[PDB]
Image (spheres, rainbow, N blue to C red):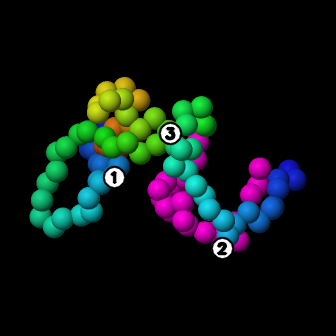
Amino acid sequence: YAWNRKRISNCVADYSVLYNSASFSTFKCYGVSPTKLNDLCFTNVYADS
Amino acid sequence: NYNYLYRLFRKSNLKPFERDISTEIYQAGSTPCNGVEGFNCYFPLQSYG
């Protein structure tokens, strides 16, 4: 109910070795593209973990 | 009436006046596909309920 709101943004969503890491759960997001994240920077994206 | 099928996505974009019958799948994410085709390979086509 109190889901987070931290504005994690203006950073690097690096995923090169992350994708190849099988132990990793999931990082591909359809939002824009699974690939369009590395140099992509977020306006005001807020994490709601 | 699921006899009517429609694609889920095409790697290329549209092309006027042409019919595609390809049934393979691309490595998208989660379970992209096994080898080239087979299990854990979300079919490019889905029917109509």
Pointer 3 chain: A
Element at badge 3?
helix
Return the x and y of residue A5 as percentages of the image width and height: 81, 61
Asked whether residue A28 is in view, the answer is no
Q: Residue furthest front?
A: A17
Which dot, 2 or 1, sits closer to the camera?
A: 2
User: According to the image, label 3 marks what residue?
Assistant: A20
Left of A8 or right of it: where is B3?
Answer: left
Please state, as top left, top right, bottom left or bottom right, where the C terminus of chain B lies in the image: top left
Residue visible at 55% across and 50% down in the picture: A15
Q: Start and end of the magenta stretch?
A: A26-49
Residue visible at 54% across and 65% down in the picture: A39
Please state, as top left, top right, bottom left or bottom right, where the N terminus of chain B lies in the image: top left
Element at badge 2?
loop
Q: Contact, CB < 8 Å: mark 2 with mark 1?
A: no
The residues tagged by marks 1 and 3 sit, at their Cα atoms, a distance apart of: 24 Å
Looking at the rendered structure, which numbered label has been put on residue A5?
Answer: none
Amino acid marked by disc 3: Asn
Q: Residue furthest bottom?
A: A43
Pointer 1 chain: B
How busy is the neighbourhood of tag 3: few (under 14 within 10 Å), some, or many (20 plus)?
few
Q: Residue furthest top?
A: B39
Left of B35 or right of it: where is B22?
Answer: left
Looking at the rendered structure, which numbered label has been put on residue A43?
Answer: 2
Amino acid marked by disc 1: Phe
Residue sitting nearer the eye, B8 or A14 = A14
Pointer 2 chain: A
Q: Is residue A21 magenta?
A: no
- Counting labels gives 3
User: According to the image, label 1 marks what residue?
Assistant: B9
Are marks 2 and 3 in one subunit? yes
Which dot, 2 or 3, sits closer to the camera?
A: 3
